[PDB]
Image (cartoon, rainbow over all chains, first blue to last red; front, side, top):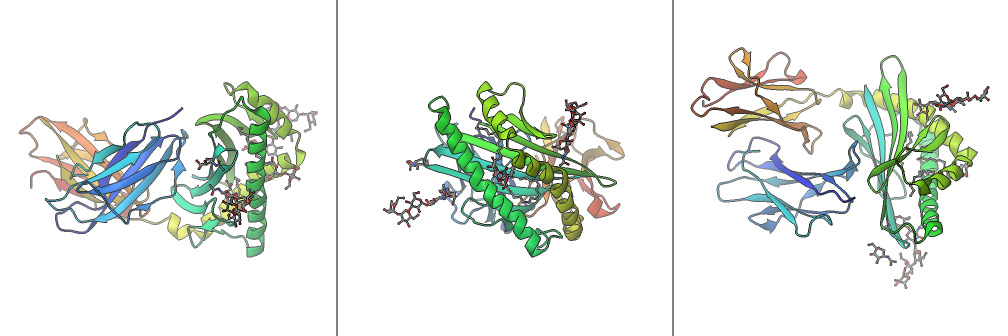
Length: 99
Length: 268
Ligand SMILES: *[C@@H]1O[C@H](CO[C@@H]2O[C@@H](C)[C@@H](O)[C@@H](O)[C@@H]2O)[C@@H](O[C@@H]2O[C@H](CO)[C@@H](O[C@@H]3O[C@H](CO[C@H]4O[C@H](CO)[C@@H](O)[C@H](O)[C@@H]4O)[C@@H](O)[C@H](O[C@H]4O[C@H](CO)[C@@H](O)[C@H](O)[C@@H]4O)[C@@H]3O)[C@H](O)[C@H]2NC(C)=O)[C@H](O)[C@H]1NC(C)=O
Ligand SMILES: *[C@@H]1O[C@H](CO)[C@@H](O[C@@H]2O[C@H](CO)[C@@H](O[C@@H]3O[C@H](CO)[C@@H](O)[C@H](O[C@H]4O[C@H](CO)[C@@H](O)[C@H](O)[C@@H]4O[C@H]4O[C@H](CO)[C@@H](O)[C@H](O)[C@@H]4O)[C@@H]3O)[C@H](O)[C@H]2NC(C)=O)[C@H](O)[C@H]1NC(C)=O
Ligand SMILES: CCCCCCCCCCCCCC[C@@H](O)[C@@H](O)[C@H](CO[C@H]1O[C@H](CO)[C@H](O)[C@H](O)[C@H]1O)NC(=O)CCCCCCC
Ligand SMILES: CCCCCCCCCCCCCCCC(=O)O
Ligand SMILES: *[C@@H]1O[C@H](CO)[C@@H](O)[C@H](O)[C@H]1NC(C)=O
């Protein structure tokens, strides 16, 4: 049966404005494994995003971790957008600027 | 305890397209990947070959090489024979490996899921369907059990090759497996104070909101989320009556810190 992806977005180091950092988008609990993940800066696709190999958990659902260098500032927003067969439209989750 | 898990994910889109990819973990550290696109199994650590010689690794890899092609043909032939009762697409996953414990004791496992659901395991000397699995699997599993050679190979792989190989991985990877990485923490927010803790390894950790010496009971631990550099991230949140955040602190205890806990005071 299809399972819908869950998306969490969080920072590797304390987010401090102007300070280079790493933003993660962890995508979990989905099936089937085919999925398209983009990270967004001001609503536009960030080009160099790196992805972990897909893997799966004890319950058999898949997960993957995306990450990108970023420098937060108070003029930029960040998000993670996912397309999967389980959803009619892509799902976007914005970074809450704190995680 | 360390659990070594070989995770295979095979997708059959139709009669002309399939792919099989694998990843291998020892505990929470990845040790191999094996892309469909690749003839050979890739190393993700300098110690991924464990204590096996190049010759012995080649032999083990050869067996998997034969298995990967054999498995793909077996599934495609099964779908042909069942046609059109079993439609493409088909997703098969396999989780196989062993759990290593004190002394030199270990338990092995080999579980298979079909369309996301556990359906078959190897146990003892045979493949079996699990109760609840679709009845059309009974016949192909009976036929696979008549393959004595495959049964003997799997019993060797589970009962012998696995724990032996992993003993070698534990010795060769000792300094990575026993690594200590220190957490850093930060705070954010009638409301919810959040203590974020990131960068620690290994996974066990204690994070609690405190008022002085007293643990705040209402502290809720989040999920452990992985960072991309083999460390962990966790938040713990506490709902607090507005105006009464003064005097609160987040405390973090972790093996990497010694007994020097991190204490982060709110509002300060
Ligand atoms: C590898 O280890 C296997 C056991 O380990 C488990 O499975 C593997 C895959 C790993 O996942 C591991 O971590 C697991 O814990 C071991 O399997 C054992 O194989 C022997 C035969 O070689 C089986 O013995 C036969 O047992 C049946 C009775 O079985 C039923 O009852 C018992 C409890 O009483 C249950 O445990 C079983 O689940 C069954 O419900 C006997 O009827 C049969 O006796 C007949 O045959 C013998 C000759 O073997 C004659 O001497 C007798 O007189 C009878 O004719 C056997 O005794 C054993 O069931 C099986 N364990 C399990 C759980 O199935 C495997 O052999 C190892 N292989 C190698 C190469 O090391
Ligand atoms: C996962 O890995 C497995 C195992 O490696 C992959 O399965 C193998 O896939 C290869 C590549 O497709 C396949 O080789 C093909 O077999 C075809 C029929 O069996 C051949 O006819 C075909 O040759 C054509 O493509 C070649 C380039 O790939 C050309 O060099 C050759 O000239 C042929 O090109 C003509 O025909 C094509 C149509 O295929 C046409 O469009 C071209 O224009 C030209 O007319 C390939 O040799 C292996 O047999 C498979 N190996 C097995 C089964 O063991 C598998 O595909 C991977 N999965 C994914 C999704 O990537
Ligand atoms: C939609 C169905 C759901 C699928 C659930 C079924 C579970 C699938 C498990 C099938 C796994 C074995 C597939 C290959 C096997 O059938 C056989 O073709 C090959 C080839 O067999 C032939 O060669 C061997 C030696 O190479 C023996 O001589 C054997 O007797 C012979 O038939 N055997 C091996 O590669 C043995 C090692 C298997 C490891 C499996 C790990 C999961
Ligand atoms: C496939 C599980 C076998 C259990 C233990 C075997 C001992 C070492 C295996 C190491 C690398 C395995 C590579 C993945 C194979 C696959 O899933 O197709
Ligand atoms: C089977 O599915 C693949 C992957 O979705 C698709 O691209 C293609 O149409 C199919 N392959 C063939 C040879 O028809």
